[PDB]
Image: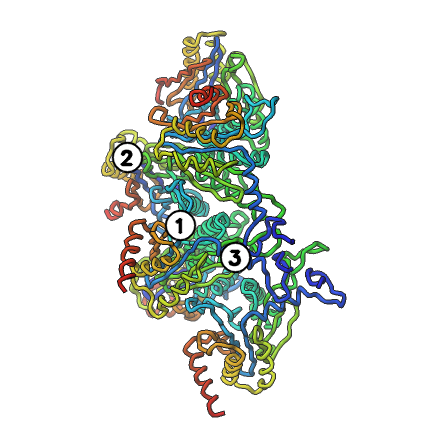
Amino acid sequence: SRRYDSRTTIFSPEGRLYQVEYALESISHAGTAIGIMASDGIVLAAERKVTSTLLEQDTSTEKLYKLNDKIAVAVAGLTADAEILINTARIHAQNYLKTYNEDIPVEILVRRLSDIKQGYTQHGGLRPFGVSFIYAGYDDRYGYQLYTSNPSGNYTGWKAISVGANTSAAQTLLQMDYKDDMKVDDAIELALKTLSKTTDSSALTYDRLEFATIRKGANDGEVYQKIFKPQEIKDILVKTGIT
Amino acid sequence: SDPSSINGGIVVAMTGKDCVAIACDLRLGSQSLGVSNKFEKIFHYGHVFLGITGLATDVTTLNEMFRYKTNLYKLKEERAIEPETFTQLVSSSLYERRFGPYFVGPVVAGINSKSGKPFIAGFDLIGCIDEAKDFIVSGTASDQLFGMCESLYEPNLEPEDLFETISQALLNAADRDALSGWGAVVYIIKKDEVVKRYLKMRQD
Amino acid sequence: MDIILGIRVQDSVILASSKAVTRGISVLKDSDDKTRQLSPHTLMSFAGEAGDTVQFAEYIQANIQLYSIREDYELSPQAVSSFVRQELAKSIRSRRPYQVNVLIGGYDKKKNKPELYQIDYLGTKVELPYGAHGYSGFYTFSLLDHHYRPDMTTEEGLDLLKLCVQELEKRMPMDFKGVIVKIVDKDGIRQVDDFQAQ
Amino acid sequence: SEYDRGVSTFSPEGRLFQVEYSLEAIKLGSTAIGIATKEGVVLGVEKRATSPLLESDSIEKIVEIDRHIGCAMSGLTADARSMIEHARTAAVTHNLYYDEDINVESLTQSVCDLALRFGEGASGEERLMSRPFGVALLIAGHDADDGYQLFHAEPSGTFYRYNAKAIGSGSEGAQAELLNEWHSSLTLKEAELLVLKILKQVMEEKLDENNAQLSCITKQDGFKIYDNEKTAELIKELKEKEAAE
Amino acid sequence: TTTLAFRFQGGIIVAVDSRATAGNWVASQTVKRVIEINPFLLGTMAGGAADCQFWETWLGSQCRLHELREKERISVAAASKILSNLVYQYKGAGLSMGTMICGYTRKEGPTIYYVDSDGTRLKGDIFCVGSGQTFAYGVLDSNYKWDLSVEDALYLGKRSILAAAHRDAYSGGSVNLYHVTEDGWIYHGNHDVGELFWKVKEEEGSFNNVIG
Amino acid sequence: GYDRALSIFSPDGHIFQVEYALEAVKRGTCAVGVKGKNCVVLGCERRSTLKLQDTRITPSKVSKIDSHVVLSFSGLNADSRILIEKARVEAQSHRLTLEDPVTVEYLTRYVAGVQQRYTQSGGVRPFGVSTLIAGFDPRDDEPKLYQTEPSGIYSSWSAQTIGRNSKTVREFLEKNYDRKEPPATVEECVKLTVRSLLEVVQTGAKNIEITVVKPDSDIVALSSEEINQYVTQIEQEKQEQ
């Protein structure tokens, strides 16, 4: 019997931190969310998990959030743990803007957050964040960027990533069709062309989605950030492969 | 020496038929020495405008304090703050510092995206609020403005006539104020479309 | 007070700063450098109260440098001056404020444009084509209002700046013991050790 | 079986095992030896490196506390660095307040009043640090009142003064030998070959001036840490007398 | 008070007087205005008698901890910084002290750092602090040369303090000399200003307007 | 059992929790430091195993602490990021209070100081990182190389390695690195660092990072080609004999 998984403050004889690993395990219980890089934009796609006939969902949101006017994130994992972060993630973002009078660079914001998640892993009386994040944004340093972070506090930059349920599947399909230059309207395509394949429901219904993207060009010498409405979805959804 | 007269400057707001106007000079100087003529006192958060006078270092800080604050608001309520909801803020804000005030004289002015009604308001350093249906003035040439506004003002001017009345008030007080001038800028705010203009004035 | 001049030209900023240091009746030094490089393309001159002056300068320098290795990216003139005004801004309302005035002149390798920010101890910041702190302005500002043009060459600016100093000498009561000049641009900072060696 | 898990728990026979185990941590260190003579005091230690790529001097097993006090430790190294640090500050401060040199035992004293700060719970005051230090000390020094003194500091919180003493993995056989060698009229050069001899004995590896460090302190020149050439020939000069008798 | 120090080929030369006064009365003519921080560093004493003495002796302890930790000689710059930093912390509280920290390490050569209670920290070659600083500066400015012998470098410092001693009422007593080298400082005695005057006048001709 | 807490000694005088932390360093990738007599060279390996991710901003395992000092690690990735930050700040605070920039030992000492501080009180867990700090003190020319462990102890080496399969790479180094005469060329000192990883890299220079540091705050990373130009020249004499 006797196991080394009773807390975060304890290394197993092999230097494992189980409590942290179990949190990393809480993610595979969340609705699938995707992020795909593009030569001109970034796409965020998620699949509402929770469901019931009488559940308001046309107004409020649950997986996609604006942190900065140039940065967005996909959530996956403990609902409450997600807001606690998202908020501080927003405050930090504004202090940078208030100090340097410039907007905060993506990696810096992702790193600051991963650094808090790191901390709840090393001090007693604390429980790590049961959250995962897909950061999609743009700064003048490195153009468009796609980042990911887990409960262990590590982060990384993908060209196309998925987190949540059936990550194996979703991850696999992408690894296959992703064309390294792929335009935006092809990523939004590939978004569903993956989410579809890895669902359960008899059919993939619009009211069960969340899309958002980041585009920019010569036109608006800056970035336009859009969070699709139930409408646009039910529509672009038909334009593809749904009656 | 009065902290609220080292840097100098002026701001004035007016209401008309479905619109408002907010204007200010451009000078920032230390005592008598003129330092700049590109120092603007009017900022805006969404469709809400705020002009600020007084100690320059505080004017700047406040803008940053409100930008910061309004961005967090929008994000949380999923909508931009309104003119009244904002006035209440900058008032409390100014007051939380009642015993070491920022040395300013703000002036809010905008249009309410729901009602569609014009709004202008003034405050003193500790945050006392003050609505008025006609005009707000604040600054070093504060009196010269009350004299101009209490003559040239006219209820319900058309945006094209408001621009002429407001400009003339600003223009002429700044000429009888030794610490205000070096240019001006005026805004005419409607439900939609906002037109900004710089005026030509004595450079002495 | 000390002398602090600065002027932005075609593609660079120039900073002038008197060399003397005086404690009461005597002059303990006539070769002081009121400058302090914050990063490869940002330079900052200062003048103010005896102790406050360089304790602050170094402090600022330390923060910028820290940020720079951490990010491995170089902070921009605009953002650098913003940070400074923040500190000084908090300073003015603290048990005891630093009494320091400054000039920051860097080269924005991102826009390929030189920029010069002038900030006083109160937290008052402004971007200008040329500036000066303290009494230094009354003797020069008119000459520069007269001859300055944005198209000026680095070579032309110096000639201009020379005139301002010559005027400072002719009508200013204090003997500032000359100035030290420095240039900031796409290639970094260098010292015109020939306005002194002249 | 059940009373050895709390640093603040008495066993039925009034014992504090955690403290005892603490000591058992020292035996794992490599040997350190101190011999006092009316000529001065000597400190020697077995270095014992895992690899030939280590830099020897990297292993500070003998260090200076002040110009008149030095020492050699044994046990947990991180725990040592902390005592050495406190000790040094203790010395320097006293100097500052009195314009004189701290008595060897009064220094040793402050080192023990430090280990005395273990225990967590809150029954009154406050001394933040959970368990006992895992290390002992051989403090060799000299002062105008009691001359050349040599001390042994234990995490228990007590200490004794010695004429000669050895700590670490080998303190078993080393202490026996020293019991049958030491005598008040030993010269400094005599003690050097003795410390050097006992190490080689209960040490292990071929005794070279790389796995053995030797130092000493005197009224004349304070604490000096013998360089490699010296120790090297002191070893030859030693190993030689072994031929005849 | 008239204290001074300067750099040159031989290293550093430090010279001071020894008069301390309360109002218009000479409470003492035996002051050690040179604080022997440690074997390699010297600090002078202007401004406040105690503040100088106290903190500089404190500073010595600091250098000692630093040397034991790094197993290396602390640098004049780092030492002078430590001092001025501690001083700056009490800016406002009313400390008082002008001072010369003098050292000569291997890497930085011979270095003088002027440091005072304002928080000022200056690097230099020649420094004079005091009520007689103006007079000392005279003899010094006109005669200094980087290539001064050691013998003459000391005589210069001596004649300088003497000049002050004579004119400045608040300066006088006996001059104290030190010479700082890459191996440490050497004391060069205490010469009574009373006797030295007559000597110089006689052997240098200077000081004519003085009948004696 | 007695391996449950940091504040408990086993009967034989151990503290297993700290020991187990070390077992994690072995989990991470391999790092190796090799000094010459005018330079110091650090090398690592890239966990190139699961990639369809970015490339631009990919960690190099090696980080600069000051203009003259770089540090490399092995073990818990996230844990490592904090030590690197803390040491970076301290490096700048030292300049602020003493003018003089830090020494390589002072930094190593500060780091290990932290690592040990996190094994003191309970309700804290030891960093699962082990690190190699290399560089040159201010206005000095003697190359330096130190290593720190999770326990809090630090040490200097002529060459050293940490991480998985560090036993192997170490054996190699030992019978090649000449104590009496260190690599006298930056090029050969590299060559030696490369050939050592070339026993755990699993072919390709696409799995090797090399950074070189010389005196006068002169540091410089290496490129993928340059690195292969050695994999090349060493794959020759390999079957050449």
Q: In the rendered view of the protein, which quadrant contains the C terminus of chain E?
A: bottom left
Identify the residue under disc 1: F46
Judge by depth and name the residue closer to the eye, B51 or A202. A202
Instruction: Tell me the subunit letter for badge 2.
Output: C
Q: Label 2: how many residues lie within 10 Å, few (<14), some (14-19) or many (20+)?
A: many
- Gap between marks 1 and 2 measured at Cα: 48 Å
Q: Position of residue C79 (x, y in %)?
A: 41, 36
- Look at the numbered disc 2 and give the secondary structure of its residue: loop
Of circles 1 and 2, the one toward us is 1
Q: Secondary structure at mark 1?
A: loop
Residue identifier under label 2: C9
- Name the foreground residue: E148 vs B42: B42
Is residue D5 toward the left or the right of residue B4 in the image? right
Precedes in sequence: disc 1 or disc 3:
3
Identify residue for label 3.
F23
Q: Amino acid at mark 2?
A: Val
Q: Can you say whether D90 is above or below F230 in the image?
A: below
What amino acid is labelled 1 in the image?
Arg
Residue D114 in sight: no
Picture quadrant where residue A117 is located = top right
In this orientation, does residue C98 appear? yes
